[PDB]
Image (cartoon, rainbow, N blue to C red; front, top):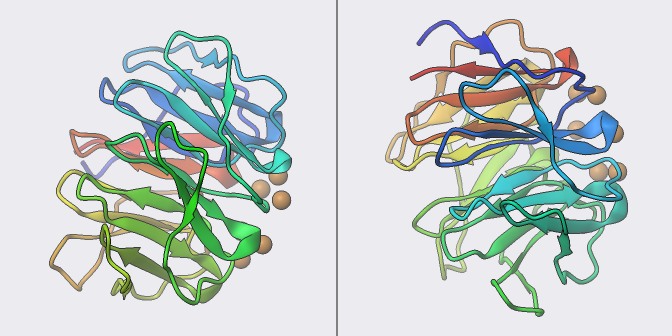
Length: 251
Ligand SMILES: [Cu+2]
Ligand SMILES: [Cu+2]
Ligand SMILES: [Cu+2]
Ligand SMILES: [Cu+2]
Ligand SMILES: [Cu+2]
Ligand SMILES: [Cu+2]
């Protein structure tokens, strides 16, 4: 599609992260209101998720079981809520410093951009010992995403670049995105196409696997967008942070 629609959220204040689950339910970190809201596909009535004590939340992710993970950036923690539960769990990360993006892979491993420590960390499901991902040279990184192959993508915000690391690899590759200006969110679809919110240029760009020529998505009227997500149908969701709204592009 070349024409976006505005999602029927209400009351958002500078939304940040966005995630979409297998059923098309959309999750948004309503950053300015210290809450996370969700909107089922076909719904015009949002629900506020029963997280407790959030402060300035940023990243959000959802796994195949519908567990929702939130970076509680103001409280230096990552919390999760299982589908149907009203009792959150704080993940046993160590030494987090102003974390930003969060992603979850098909094994349940949780990846967090530890923004103030210039690093990305991960916690296996049921593990209490995190590991650091062997990225080099990160500078105030923000978004993180992980594909079904285990490849991890990070927006190296301070360096105006996007970096990736294959599973088990110790050698990162810098993606051939061009013209970036303070990149923010990142997402990856089932085909390996990487989507990046080009925050300072009010646009969203993508790079197909195997390609080194990017495409700009036909969003319009964005102001300082932040989070991005893509569902299994190819629909792309962007938190239009500056306009307190979430927009989507079908196809
Ligand atoms: Cu703002
Ligand atoms: Cu804030
Ligand atoms: Cu902060
Ligand atoms: Cu910073
Ligand atoms: Cu910046
Ligand atoms: Cu800005």
